[PDB]
Each structure stands twice: as structure tokens, then as C-alpha cells.
Image (cartoon, coloured by chain):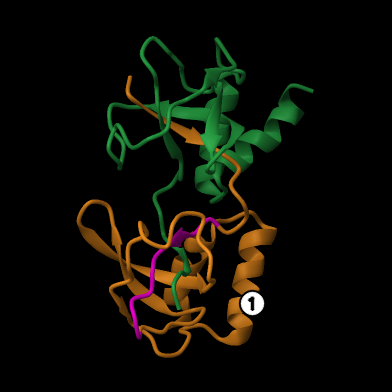
Chain colours: A orange, B green
Amino acid sequence: MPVAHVALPVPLPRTFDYLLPEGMTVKAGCRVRVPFGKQQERIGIVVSVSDASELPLNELKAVVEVLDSEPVFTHSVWRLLLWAADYYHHPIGDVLFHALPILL
Amino acid sequence: MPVAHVALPVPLPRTFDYLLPEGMTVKAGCRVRVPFGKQQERIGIVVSVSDASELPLNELKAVVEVLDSEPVFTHSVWRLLLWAADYYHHPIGDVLFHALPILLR
């Protein structure tokens, strides 16, 4: 058949890059609505903000809107969760979202 | 200001789709050489083979070479591993490649 879905041992935090439009600011631990797939949106959680993407600064899509001015996560809670993710081999996205509810 | 590394609640097994050139055939549980990054190669294990990707069937990179005629994993072992990865929430690629050196050795 066509598409071979393959598995690879990507680096620890597997994240998806998106560009921040002019004047839009967000820090680590903030929820943001971003594009996903040819047309729908979805809530995500910003893990970090760098000045380098594994692909060009132009074919990355842009965040649509920040939903939190301040981290929905405690400085401690955040450090902890990222650790657990890494220590027990769980994807950051999975820990973070499954962790959001219990928190609120 | 520019970029941001975002965590997403992606579906159970987060896999990387690769196109199969004409005449190239591979089954679940087989290792394959695939591109990665603007120029490096790497070894991975096919989890499944379908007729569709979240991306255009032309924007995907192509598998380079299949390293296994047959599943390097037993039909039981395989079923178990995928389950283990799912139920305990471990990256399928992470469970598959670590176990290989155990099961074989």
C-alpha cells in the first residue's frame, strides 16, 4: 500500500513548531489554539519558546490565539510534570493534557 | 518571538508516515531505513501500512530500504508490545526499540 507509518525514537519532548505572529506573546505553560491538519484547530500547550525551528521560519503555521496570560501550571507543578514525562517515558503532550483537568 | 515548541494530545501511536516507492513492500513489525532531518538516515519499525496519511501522498519522504523480509518480532510479542505501549502510555517507538535487544538477545 501507500503510506508506511513508521516509528522512530525522536528526541525526548516531541513537539510541533508554530510561528508567533507580530506582537503575540506567550510563555511556557500557556494554552494556545493552533492549526492542525488541512483545516481544523486545536488547543495545545506551549512547552518552550526558542528562536530556532527544525524547518524554515516561513513554512511553519502560526498560532491563532493565546488562551492564557499566565501559566495554567505552577512553576513547581510544571517542572514536576515535564520530569515525569521524561523519567517514565510518557509523551509530554499526554502528561500535560491528562494533567490539566485534575489540576483545575 | 518567532517559534515555540508545543506539546499536543496526539492519538495513541504517534508515527511518522513515509511513502513506499513502486515495487517496495513491507509488513507490520519490519525494520526500515528512512530519511530524518534535511539529510540524515535512521532505522525504524513499521507499525502499520494503510492507504492514507494526514499529509499529501507526495509530500511524504520515501522509505529507503526494508531491512526485514519478515517481522523481527513474533506475532504474540508484537501484539503484546503495542498493547503495553498503549495501556501504560509509552511511545510505541520507545517500547519497540528498547525491547528488541532484550527479546533477541
Q: Is residue B54 left or right of residue A98?
A: left
Image quarter of the C terminus of chain B: top right
Q: Report the span colored magenta.
A: A14-23
Front residue of B42 and B100 = B42
Image quarter of the N terminus of chain B: bottom left
Q: Position of residue A29 (x, y in %)?
A: 49, 79
Vertical order, B53 against A49 (above or below):
above
Q: Amino acid at mark 1?
A: Arg
Mark 1, residue position: A79
Q: Position of residue B42 (x, y in %)?
A: 61, 33
Q: Is residue B63 left or right of residue A77?
A: left
Tell me, yes or no, whether the highlighted magenta stretch contains residue B40: no
Q: Is residue A100 left or right of residue A40?
A: right
Tell me, yes or no, whether the highlighted magenta stretch contains residue A17: yes
Q: Is residue A53 left or right of residue B73?
A: left
The image shows a total of numbered marks equal to: 1
Which residue is at 32% across, 62% downward?
A: A61
Which residue is at 33% across, 19% downward?
A: A1
Q: Position of residue B50 (x, y in %)?
A: 33, 27
Q: Main secondary structure of the magenta part?
A: loop
Which residue is at 53% across, 55% downward?
A: A14
Q: Secondary structure at mark 1?
A: helix
| Quadrant of res A40 | bottom left
Q: Please identify the residue farthest to the left as the structure is shown.
A: A39
Q: Position of residue A69 (x, y in %)?
A: 40, 90
Which residue is at 48% across, 80% downward?
A: A103
Label 1: how many Cα within 10 Å (few below 14, some 14–19, many 20+) = few
| Quadrant of res B81 | top right
